[PDB]
Each structure stands twice: as structure tokens, then as C-alpha cells.
Image: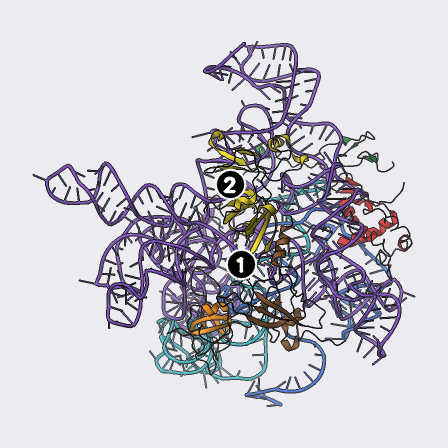
Chain colours: A brown, B yellow, C red, D orange, E green, F purple, G cyan, H blue
Amino acid sequence: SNIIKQLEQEQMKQDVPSFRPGDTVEVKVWVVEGSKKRLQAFEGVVIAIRNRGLHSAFTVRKISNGEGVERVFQTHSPVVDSISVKRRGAVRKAKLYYLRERTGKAARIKERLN
Amino acid sequence: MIGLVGKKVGMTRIFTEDGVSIPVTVIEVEANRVTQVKDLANDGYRAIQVTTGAKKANRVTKPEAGHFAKAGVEAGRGLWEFRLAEGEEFTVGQSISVELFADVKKVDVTGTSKGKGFAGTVKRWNFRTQDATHGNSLSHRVPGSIGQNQTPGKVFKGKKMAGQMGNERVTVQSLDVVRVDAERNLLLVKGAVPGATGSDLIVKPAVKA
Amino acid sequence: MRHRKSGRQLNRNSSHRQAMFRNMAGSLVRHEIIKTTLPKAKELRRVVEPLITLAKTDSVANRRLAFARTRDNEIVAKLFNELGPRFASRAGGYTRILKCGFRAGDNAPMAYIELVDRSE
Amino acid sequence: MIQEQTMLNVADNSGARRVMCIKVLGGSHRRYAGVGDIIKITIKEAIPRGKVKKGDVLKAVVVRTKKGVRRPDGSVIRFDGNACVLLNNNSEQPIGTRIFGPVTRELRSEKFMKIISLAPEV
Amino acid sequence: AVQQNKPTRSKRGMRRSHDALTAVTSLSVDKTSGEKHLRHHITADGYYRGRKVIAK
RNA sequence: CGAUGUCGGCUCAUCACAUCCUGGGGCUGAAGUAGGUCCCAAGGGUAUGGCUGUUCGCCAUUUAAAGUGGUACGCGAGCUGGGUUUAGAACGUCGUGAGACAGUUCGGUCCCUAUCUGCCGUGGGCGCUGGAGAACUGAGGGGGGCUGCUCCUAGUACGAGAGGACCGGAGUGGACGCAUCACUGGUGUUCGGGUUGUCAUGCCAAUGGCACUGCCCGGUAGCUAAAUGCGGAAGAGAUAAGUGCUGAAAGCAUCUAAGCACGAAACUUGCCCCGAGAUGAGUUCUCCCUGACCCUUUAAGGGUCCUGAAGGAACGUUGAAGACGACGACGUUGAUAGGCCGGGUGUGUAAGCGCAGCGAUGCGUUGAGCUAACCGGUACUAAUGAACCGUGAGGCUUAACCU
RNA sequence: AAUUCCUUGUCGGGUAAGUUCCGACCUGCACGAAUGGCGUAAUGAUGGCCAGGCUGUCUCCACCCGAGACUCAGUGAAAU
RNA sequence: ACACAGGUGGUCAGGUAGAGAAUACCAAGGCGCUUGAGAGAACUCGGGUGAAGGAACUAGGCAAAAUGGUGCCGUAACUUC
């Protein structure tokens, strides 16, 4: 049997960005609220793993206070209208959990200068 | 009115334009082979032996082999005899596809629970333990006071104590149909289903509806 | 209780669950036949066949296979010379266990493991 | 979770930072409170511009949580701190003139004509 | 300590009606050496499953 | 008195209603919303904090409810031992003083190898009339229900106003108990990263130990609920308390006698799990056996010689099955387990070599090397060949068909 | 009050709510001078109370490791 | 009363660290335990790791858990100084 793999493939979108931990993003959603179908826009930072296929969480933080203001955007969700990639940081690690106990001025996703 | 058997292939989330992701279970329902149709009403009742899969021929004995021989060369395991009342079905041996649910909104699924062994009172009856703070010793995973002091002389039968959990029959009473495609053997349902390889997953239309 | 866990526990100290067999693999590369209890022969066969599949490949700034422990100096004349090249054209299974029952009357089942390329 | 004896901050404008939950309200044997839910509260802190004394007992509506929300649209949204709006013990409704923060989208449709009219973003 | 005389020999003599035995159940004879052995076990003659395993 | 543990609380509730809430039926000296009250159904259900060791008491806050009454003023081979109760004495009282006071206080004794009666699970067994298996049935047993909230009746009625409802309707949280691993989090002593101290390998380089898995950061499968997910319904039937129609015993009258229609959450039917020890042993299908003589105060038992089906157990590689038994998958007629070949995922770019820098360190070789639990293939190690147990068409009687 | 039953003392603060705490009242059933009267700094392997701190004490424990409980072999008690 | 998880005065003393005669790895030297073969379940007990809430636990912060080291800045009332 293969029908489950074709079912996830018709629910996934025909192109989406391949972002990773240490990336910044700008996202637009229509919030599924009511008759106006009104748009909401946001810009933030990714330190959570994407990860792969239909069930990507796409967890984004603002990284500007000692509390991250976390939101789960879901890459393949039909409530999303645009997903845009901005910049990438000088990190090499993918876990990055130490940044959850720092404020935004101590979580600038590294610069290194090698 | 009857039911079908088909095998689980996985669980996923379909995603919907209401924002909710709707967790769904995928079942592949190959046409149920039909080993015998009993429309002749012997002893005052009608039935159908819907049949799915077959058992390895080194573990099929002659008392079972002759019980599938009159409808094919393959035999054993799930014969599945269902009774027929207030409904006519075609009189001759003919297999039944999953299109039986293509005009059904709600279903139920019955199978066999996972093995949980020994259990004990706490893991069988989901029972409140005794607190180990401020003393108490030698027993904390017991129900306490199994009868009402001195005048019972006895314990009552079938009470919420002891026993072993799992490896038994279990029903999930309500699931929503999402997609049916009999050319692909496909059944797609909103929800989750009990047990793994011990579970037969007998799926039925809602008899309340 | 067990639902994915299966690995044989055997010994009280955590490292002794491997050391008992690391130490006895040195005796097996020496004598090519060993007498020990059936669960100890099964745990002796564990990981040492993948160590012969590691003795199959060309190594660089590393001679550490079987030499990092047990202080034997005959292994460095067997390895890459005949231990490896005698077992690389067989496709797996480098030991035969010769499974037997109780040795005489106690509850100890016996095994007579051999390194499979032996002659008589 | 927001349960009995849980500490929150005041979102009614120029309010105190420590106020404590004592009853979840509404019945059906329900436990805990979510965002947009009404609770019984006690005032653990007083401030010079504050409208209420320490030890007073009132009603409040929850407007922000660290745990956040995940069920109305099936996806998770989390916030900074644990916050609530205080109500008058005689006449009910908010006691200041404004409420702080953008709040939940479900709170913009809630049973409170004086809370859905204020300037929060969402 | 608490006991009503002894456990009756009627109940003790009923204790063997349910299995508690640990002993090998049957032995068989090899078709290459005529030697007596256990099932799925090598002979004292070095023969098993129709083949010669070792020289003895 | 040859033995009868004490107070409250916890912990466990149990069993009721002279009914706390919910369902249903009538009133108020009840305009509505309120306040006050009589009573059928025992079917569904019936609080947390403060002060105190507290029953009691006052005091903060809920719920549709926190009410009345029993159970060693309910639970010690239950928990707590805070209170009451000894063994030193501190303060007050009576007395010269021992001793006395329904006085206050610091500290102060709660320990168990399951014999029988009970109950639960798991094997085994005898019963069932030749032997065997698979599915079915239902005499019998348990589960469940009540409350809120939005929308409708309706801003109707009643009410100068202030306010502000019935009874039949539609939808849906949550409680309760269980089921999933898609994900979402925690864990994860078969994995990995960083690192403090030390040991050996001659040394150094580089590895492998030990110090709680040395620690610190992390983690797959699996486990786990916070993760997400679901139902006890409707309809009909009968019908208590209750509302009535027609109406007799009885020229008149009556809610009853005959003839009838209504009348509840529940009940009965209904949903689901279990169930032939139901010796009342049920219904149905499927497999198999075609030898011959003999004995008895011989319609039932017992031998000899031949012969051994269907089926069972033993042997065995493994487990989303398991204390042990027992049981699914699977056995060379083979990918069940390990090993191999290739890839996947995890780990994150090693060593050696070449270089940048005074060096710590950094770069290229290098998406390196390594690899828990997966997955496209593959018989290298293991997953018999026989023997054992089970027989030979099966009693007595009648009814029905043909010889 | 290490003394007071009367009381749930009374009044103030503390607490959501303070028979416990401290500061006061005098109407002390029964304080008072080396059987010491009343005060007191530093101090406590302390009787009580307040705030601050952190926490599996609690909401509510969940996973995970280790032995015994087990299946065998060798041995192998007592009260009752 | 035992070939007993117990007790027993003084003497010595090397490496790495470390304040050290602590502790942890090693030396000189000693020992692997007078039961073996396993299997890895309720339940009790001794340990390892932890999300959001938080003394509400309980008569009682009892117990547990953080705080803890070696330098520097800084540091109230009161006092028998």
C-alpha cells in the first residue's frame, strides 16, 4: 500500500522555503476569523527545527525580550498567504536551547567573524 | 446492517480550510472475499461469511481447510460470519468492496487492545494512590478498605480491584467518514483506532443513525 | 516492562555486560574455539562479527581494533594478514555456536563456539 | 496551568503586578481557566496609582498566558507573563479606562460589550 | 503463628495433579550414526541434521 | 477484667430519605424577576479555603447541589498521632506538706514470613455419549445517565416604571471513563555533543577506562498526557404520582366499574463488553477412521493378535503476548532473529596530511569519519528427520422410508 | 503574662479569612521582691509568628536505573 | 555460641592533583569475596532525569531542593567597643 504517501503529497504545497534553525522570516496569514478574511503579517526568528514533509511545525519567536512570544505557523497550512525568507545567522548548532534563557540583544543568531 | 474488515496503513493530519488540521487514520480495505451467502434461512436466520486474508498452509488443519474450500483455494483465520435482518443481499458468492460506505456519514470500529499484562488495581481501574508524604509505609498502590468494616463478613464480586489489562476486545463508538475510493481500496476516517497486529478493526455503519 | 528493550542484562556492573566478552574475544582470537554457557556464547558472538567486518577495510593512523584493550601482541600479526582476508568473501556469519543443553545436571546450558574458517 | 493559588499580573491600565486566583467559576465540575475565561481573584499587591487595596476579593478575566492557546484554530500561540483584567464588585466591567496587550482573537467576540470595544490589536 | 492442626494429606495428595516438573521430555536416534540424542541437539558421535559437524 | 486501643481530620466510602440539587406534580397571605410552602420518582448526582488538633464555632470564596439520619458518636493485621493520657519539671491555684485542680506548657512509645471464610487473574481438569476444530446463540452479569453555555419561543405576557418569565424546539463545551503517538511536550544507564580531574598504552600524537551515565548540554525507538480525541442518544412501548373523556353500580351524582386518550430524567425496548458449570450442557458448519476372533449369573463389562485417521503435545527462530504458565507472527517448502550488501535517519566535518597565526585557536582535504531500535535486497549462523499421545464409523429405544 | 477559665477576650496591624503572632486595655476566678521582682546586648544541631528564597511537600507525580520478589540447580529454619 | 554486612590500642604513608593523612585515579603490595546458571513482572525500598502551576502540603517548610568555593566591589539598626 502507498495511498497514504500520495495523500500527504496532494495536501503539501507545490513550492515552500527550506529554512532551518538560525534563519529570520516574514509570514502572512488570513487568520480564519470571519467574513472579511483579513490578513495578518509578522516578522521573527527561527531556532526550532522545521523539520520535514507535511507536519512541519514552523515555530517562530520574536527574540526581543526574556520571553520569546512563540507561535506555530505550519508551512503547509491553507491559512497561510505568503512565506518569505529574510537572512541567515552564523550559528552551526541546530538545538540552540540556551537562547531561550537570554534576551534578544544576547540572541542575535551569531556573527562569529572567522 | 453488517460491516467490513481492512488493514491499517497509518495515521496523519489532512489539513482543512477551517485552520484545524483534522487528524485522520488510513485503512486499506481490499474487497471482503465472501466464502458463503446464507439467504436460505436455515434454523430461522440469514447470514454472510465476509472473509479477509488467509493463514499459512503449514498452520491450517483439515477441520478448517474444508470450511473455505467451497469458495476458493486459499483458507484460514478470519471467516467473519455476520447475520442478515431487514435487508436483501445477492444470493450467490460475490465479494464486497468498500463502496458499501460511499453513502454513510458515521461509523464505529472494534478490535483488540494492546497487551498491558499484570496491571494491578491502579493501572487497571485508574485509581487514586495513597500519599507517601507525612508517613505511610509498605503499601501505597492499593485501593484501601475493600469492604465496609466488620458486619459484611465478605467481599462483593466484580469490584474495581485487581485483574489484568489489555489483550481483550474494545470498541470506539463514533468516527467521521472523510474519503472513500473503492478503485484504490481506500477508507479515510477522522479519528484514531485501538491496537496493532492483534486488532482486526471490524468497521460498521452507525446503527443509531 | 519490555516493549522495545530486549538486550541481555546478565551482569551487575554496567560495563561488565561488555567487558566479559571484550576480554573473552581475546581468548577466541587466540584459541579459535571456546567452551562457555549458551547466553555468554550468544553475547560473545554479539558485536565481534561487525569487528571482523571492520578488519575488512583499509585503516589510517588507527591500529586500535582489539589492541586498545587486553594487551595482546599476536593480534597485530593476525589482523590484516589472515584475520579479515579469510572472512571477507563469505557475506556475513563468522562464528558457529554449536548450541547444546545442560553440561551435566545443573541449570547451565553449554555452547562450543568456533571461528568459522577453521580446518580439521 | 491557571489553577487555584496561581499568581498573575493586572492588565487593567496602571495596575499591580501580583494578583492570585482563588476560584475558576462557571460550574459543570470544570477545573483550570484558559484565555478569555472569568475567575475569582485576591489582590496580593497594592501601588500608589492602584484602584484596589491589598487583600480585596474580586472577579477577573484572563487575557495573557505563558502556556498560551492551541484549540480554536488547531495551532499554538504563546505569550509573555500571565495576565488578567479586574472587574468591579458592585457593577462589574473593567475598573480603569484601557486594557493592556493585543489579547486573543476569540476574546474580540466574547460575552463582554465593554472589553470588545477597547483598542487591543487582535 | 496460626494453623488449624496441619494442611490435610487430602489437599497435599492433590498438589501433583497440576504440573511442576522440570526434565527433558523425549530422546531420539540419529540417521547417520545410530546414536541417541535430544531434538535440535548434536550427538556424542559429532553428527547432526544429516551432516558430520566434527571428527570424534 | 485467663484482654473490648482513644478525639478530630485524612483515606475508603457505604446504605438510606422524614429529598440538598436535578426530573415531575400542586400552592403562596406568589403581578413577572424574587421571597415563603406542600410531596411523587431513590433513577442521575450532592464543596474548597482561613483560625484551631477540633466535633462545635466564627470567618473568606464557589456549585445545579454542599441538606437529614445510621455504620464500635463508621474506618488502626488503615494513615496521621496534631488533641486526650503516665515516666523530668516551668508558671498559677488548695494545703504545713505528701497529696489535691474536669488548669496552662517543652519534650514524649503506633514494629507482623497469609492458616482458614471472601474476591480477582491465569493455567490445568472432569462433565458432556465416536473423536476434533472453527464461528454462532443468550438463561446470567457489569457499564452509562444529572449540570452549564449560545441560538429560538420573547423584550412576547405581566409590569405607570424599574424591570422581565413558562412549554414542546436546534446546537455545543466541560465532568466521567477510556482509546490514539499524526503530531505537541517530559523522559530515554543499548546514541551523541562539550568538558573538569586522573590512569595506562615507552613518550608525544591519538584512543580506551574510572570518578552518580564523573559532570554539563542534549536525544531515537519505546514509555508517558499536558499532546487530540470520543459516548451512554433518538423513537416506540408500558405507566406511578398527576391531568381528564365517556359513564355504570345509584330517576339524582361520581376520575372507575366496563370502553378509552394523555401522563418522567427513569423503567421496558435500545448502545457495548462478558456469558452453555444454562450438567437446562443450546444453533450451524467443517475434518477423519471400513480389522478379526474370544469370555461372563453375556443388552453391560473384559481379553488376544493385527492396525493407528482427523486432531494434540513435544522440538524451534521471535514478539506492539507475558510473573511463571499460557498465546500472535514464523521454521531450509525460509528473510522470523543475528551477520552481510547498499541506502536511510541520527551524530556534525574526526584522525592522518597540507596550510593560516607568536600562540590558544582556525581553515582546506571533508555534506568527514562514526552510527540504538529502519528498510530495498541477501541463507553466511540458526529456525529437523523420527518417535510420543489420539484409533478402527461409535449404546438402548421408538417413530418415519425403501428392501 | 510560659500565670487568665470567663472568650471566638477586646481594639490595632498582619491573613482573602489570624482560638496561633505582636502591640495595647484592667474588670488580675488565682503577678510581685534572692523558694529572687522587672529589664538585656551577642547567641541557639530552639516553643510560636512575618516577609523574602527555592523546592516532587502539594496540584499530580511521569519516565528511567538497581536489588529482592521468579524459573532452575546445590544446600536449607522456628513459633504454630 | 556461627569460617557473621559488627567491634578492636599503637606503627608506616610513594605519583597526579588537592589546604589534606579528604577524594578519585594509579604505585609497592594485596584481593575478585566457600553458591552457581539465568530471566528481566505486580509490589516495596535505594537511586537517575524532568514541562507548566507552587507551602495551597501537613497539626508543622518536617523532609526535600536551591544557596555553598576562591578573589574584588559593597554592607543597616544596635553594642558590654
Depth check, front residue: C68 or A86: A86
* Mark 1 or 2, closer to the camera: 2
**Residue at the location (60% across, 69% down)?**
A27
Depth check, front residue: B170 or H18: B170
- The local crowd at label 2, few if under 14, some if 14 to 19, many if 20 or more residues have their Cα within 10 Å, is some
**Residue at the location (88% across, 44% down)?**
C118
* Snapshot quadrant of residue G74: top right
> In this picture, is F214 found above or below G20?
above
> Which secondary structure lies at badge 2?
loop
Residue C25, visible in the rendered structure: yes
The residue identified by callout 2 is: B2
Q: Is residue B150 left or right of residue C71?
A: left
**Mark 2 is on which residue type?**
Ile
Q: Earlier in the sequence, mark 1 or mark 2?
A: 2
The residue identified by callout 1 is: B131
> In this picture, is D40 found above or below C45?
below
Asked if the residues shown at circle 1 and circle 2 are in contact, with their CB atoms under 8 angstroms apart, the answer is: no
**Mark 1 is on which residue type?**
Asp
Q: Find residue H6 and report its horizontal and vertical position in percent.
A: 70, 59
